[PDB]
Length: 387
Length: 148
Image 1 (spheres, each protein chain N blue to C red):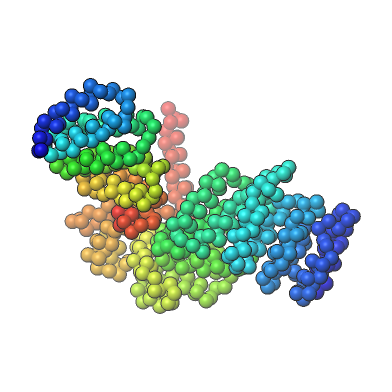
Image 2 (cartoon, rainbow over the protein chains, first blue to last red):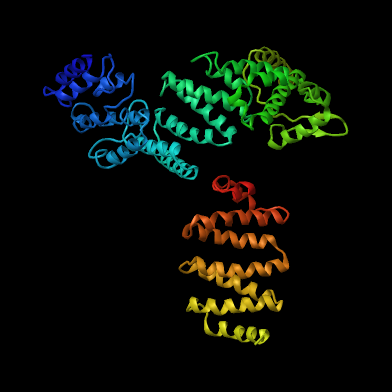
């Protein structure tokens, strides 16, 4: 419609009297193509608000505005949307060209102040620009080169670092794609979870970004066994910033399956995409032992009891003793168990390894314990006081 | 002619007499002939001592990868006869560093596989811990992945 022209004039005029970045015919094209409230990009503060409801194409049109830009509003603002636009429009060949066009020390430092990176808010070009070259090559091309790019993103991250969330979230997003490709699903599950916690306060709070990241979280948790169980999924959202159904149904069923330990409930939850993958099934047994083990141990623990039999663990898993013998032996190897198995006693004497976290039940019990300890100590104290 | 014993002896007097360290390029060639002669003779020891001295000297000087590799190629033939797998791992570990900078990664990634692989043969390795950590030990090639 006519909002491109209306906003852009009033703001251009109001600041410096000569309209400093606005020019009449650029406006004519953007009006002609669109018919919406938002325009594919705009200029200054208006550009932030106004993003495409279709595809940014007017990125080449914008570059003219970029030479003019600085006088009106600062230079640091430019990369925030324009490099992000290139990533959105899915043109590989042009995305690569512009990072070289703009580059570093040619328009990105004359006398301006450097903060680096600009996923959200804004900073200086350089550390943003590095993240974009590395992202477009990683998807496109060889794995071996995609790693070398990851290393370069890593050395730059360490050198220069900032107090906003923007840098951290950029490091996380770039690396995650690589893991997704690999059969190293366990590492992917660690990575995606870190990104989740950074993401929700600030930086990329668009629903799209939550929805893709959540889907990756669910697939990876099932493939992995890398970090605890389904407590991590409760605390952070992948089914209540977004849909509770359509491949997040699988989560609620995963919770029922782990406690119960039914193989059939594991079989039914998985649908063809997640299931085909060779990786998951082994790692299903690992998650089941860890959860079951945590439940028996809490129960017995009330002073210092940590003795649980073969019979308790065999029962829990729903596997005979011999399968369990081999299975625990694999699980201790990893160090998910730091007890020890005495074969001919038929008792497992366990030295704590459990995380013990997420409280509601545990606090009531803790409170009871804190009080008891305080009494025990108090008597000791009394005796000293006496002589 | 087949005068192994006589060639080895004439070489032994020469290298010490000519050179303390004045010219390496010439010294190294003479040393190379000795090493070859030493394997055949069964006299394991004289070569081992010579290889160790020359290696230190070259590393300290301007470095050249080629020179080194030539010491090593001879050494392993002696090492098979004895059988110290630990010994080959170490000697190869220091040449891995020279390979790192100089030489392309097609030579390099098999060398990495080879050092960890000597350490499999022997019981334990202190040395192995250092190698397993590297990030080029768990990507790339088939052979690297199989080894990790």
